[PDB]
Length: 185
Length: 185
Ligand SMILES: *[C@@H]1O[C@H](CO)[C@@H](O)[C@H](O)[C@H]1NC(C)=O
Ligand SMILES: *[C@@H]1O[C@H](CO)[C@@H](O)[C@H](O)[C@H]1NC(C)=O
Image (cartoon, rainbow over all chains, first blue to last red; front, side, top):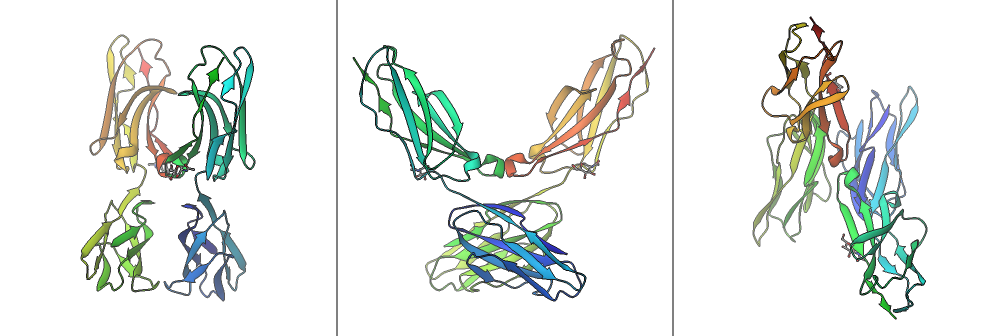
């Protein structure tokens, strides 16, 4: 009965997408789409198929097509996913002066970023990875202890986010905070 | 000036896709698309934007939008890629009886399959991989020698193709030939 194409779509936050609602029955009494998103109707055969441009999609949504055929009423849902890199990625303020032999805690804060299911927050010592974790909460915080050694000198520590959309057909988008320099003694 | 969305698309062989040709200039003297593909024109503002449904795309194509603005004439191309698993995947006919201690050659033939840039042909001994190679030519052949040992008994050999579209946002589609049993002595 009812069908929608694409059934799944990934688009940048605030973007637009074309959705086609279709129905296989001879005489559709009604065919349309239910969604609160700003919409515009275009024209194909008009009757068995309808095309809509959904615009300024700010967050995930599942618009659904529908058609009332004489045989029965059915629906078809399309899942829209919006992406955007974090609006802010920084390490919580930490004293520059740090006691040798004592423990220090790094805390990264990531505000925003979606889809969260593909966003990872990582803490680094120079170019080395210290911790990796899925981004959870708002802001998404990630923490780790670091035993201050003399080895830790002009070691710059940083936080990085990885929005990996490659499995969706796009790319990995990375972001980095300002570095933190450990001044010991 | 001219723009096209999507600028790149991957679709199954014989499928359809919606293409929107746009132009940023005030008064476009002309706006359209050049492509030999079966097309249908839908309607958005009509003037600065036009939508077309390209149908039954059988092979890769690069339809281009165009617009003649007073400022100048420009173009924008969209690259369409069609996919389809091989129409046939089999090992060249080989005698069932095979001399111990002598060399045997396996030869897989893969007819079709696209995009070829993501199709790999692999030869296997049971579930073990013996050879892997990008699919080249038509039919795409892949060969390997196998030193017949007594170890090679009711060893079934097979050929598999991997159409890896995961980097495009889809999945890996696999195909396998009939197995070949080595009857020695
Ligand atoms: C994050 O990286 C994107 C590109 O990947 C860039 O456009 C954006 O400005 C960066 N965001 C921040 C907060 O630095
Ligand atoms: C190859 O696999 C696809 C699904 O991945 C299947 O639909 C098709 O029939 C297979 N082709 C052959 C020749 O077996």
